[PDB]
Image (spheres, rainbow, N blue to C red):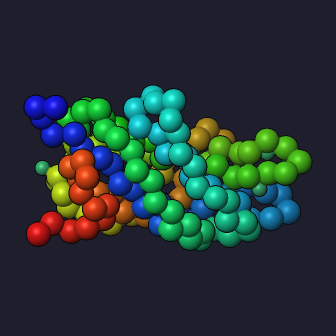
Amino acid sequence: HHHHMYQLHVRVVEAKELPKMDTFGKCDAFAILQLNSSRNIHRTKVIEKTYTPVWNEEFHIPLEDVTIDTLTVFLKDEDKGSSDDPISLIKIPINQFPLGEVVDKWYSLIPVKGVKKGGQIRLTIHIAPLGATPFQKTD
Ligand SMILES: [Ca+2]
Ligand SMILES: [Ca+2]
Ligand SMILES: [Ca+2]
Ligand SMILES: [Cl-]
Ligand SMILES: [Cl-]
């Protein structure tokens, strides 16, 4: 290639202020990550029965065009006797992240229709050139 080929490294750290998504429980949250409308989707594990889940899971997503790519983060509640319940989502433009910076930030999610509040999610995001160590700060 005659241009840089960037990688999106994302740590899904934790969430807070989640809504009650179960009549007899609290929330069993997991997060789904999707670049643009890609068929490669990533999902975290489920953290049962808490409004403040901690996942600390890392994902590595090749980028097509840092000037236009978007990362959608979608929170859902796992259920056992019914289908999972959508909670909230945020679409994050990749072009807002300085190349090579490790950015650790909280994000407000937008609740889906019918959900009272969307929560916040903490993501550590690092746009780095191909081969660079994920989450390694610039030197
Ligand atoms: Ca539920
Ligand atoms: Ca549930
Ligand atoms: Ca359900
Ligand atoms: Cl609620
Ligand atoms: Cl930049």
Q: Position of residue 19 (x, y in %)?
A: 64, 59
Q: Position of residue 39 (x, y in %)?
A: 51, 30
Q: Image point 44% across, 45% down: which residue?
A: 90
Q: Answer left or right for 68 relative to 47.
A: left
Q: Answer left or right for 29 relative to 103.
A: right
Identify whether 98 is placed above or below 13.
above
Q: Nearer the viewer, residue 115 or 94?
A: 94
Q: Nearer the viewer, residue 96 or 130?
A: 130
Q: Position of residue 129 (x, y in %)?
A: 21, 49
Q: Tell me the quadrant of the picture where the N terminus can be found.
A: top left
Q: How many marks?
A: 0
Q: Image point 17% across, 53% down: which residue?
A: 98
Query: In which image quadrant can residue 16 be found?
Result: bottom right
Q: Image point 62% across, 55% down: which residue?
A: 30
- Please state the quadrant of the image where ligand 2 appears: bottom right
Q: Nearer the viewer, residue 133 or 68?
A: 133
Q: Position of residue 71 (x, y in %)?
A: 39, 42
Q: Image point 80% across, 65% down: which residue?
A: 25
Is residue 32 something that shows in the picture? yes
Q: Answer left or right for 16 relative to 20.
A: left
Identify whether 136 is placed above or below 82.
below
Is residue 16 something that shows in the picture? no
Q: Tell me the quadrant of the picture where the C terminus can be found.
A: bottom left
